[PDB]
Image (tube, rainbow, N blue to C red):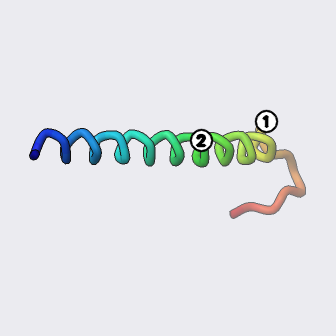
Amino acid sequence: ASKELELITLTVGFGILIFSLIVTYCINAKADVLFIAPREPGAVSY
């Protein structure tokens, strides 16, 4: 009984991680498209 539940939870846990990994990954790229190379004069500092 406990094992069955553990497995179900594990699957849902691994599934959630994969979803997040894909989300964070997409963001990492969307950020690299801006902070590509060092900023040059004129750019707006944070």
The kind of residue on which mark 1 rests is: Ala
Q: Position of residue 14 (x, y in %)?
A: 38, 39
The kind of secondary structure element at disc 2 is helix
Q: Position of residue 38 (x, y in %)?
A: 77, 39
Q: Classify 10 Å Cα crowding around label 2: few (below 14), some (14-19), many (20 and above).
A: few
In the orientation shown, which residue stands out farthest toward the top? 37
Q: Indicate whether 16 appears above or below 37.
A: below
Left or right, 37 with respect to 41, comes to left
* Residue depth check, mark 1 versus mark 2: number of the one nearer the observer: 2
Q: Position of residue 35 (x, y in %)?
A: 75, 44
Q: Quadrant of the C terminus?
A: bottom right
The kind of secondary structure element at disc 1 is loop
Identify which residue, 2 or 19, lies in the foreground.
Answer: 2
Left or right, 42 with respect to 20, comes to right
Mark linked to residue 7: none
Residue at position x 24%, y 39% from top? 7
In the orientation shown, which residue stands out farthest toward the left? 2
Q: Which residue is mark 1?
A: 37
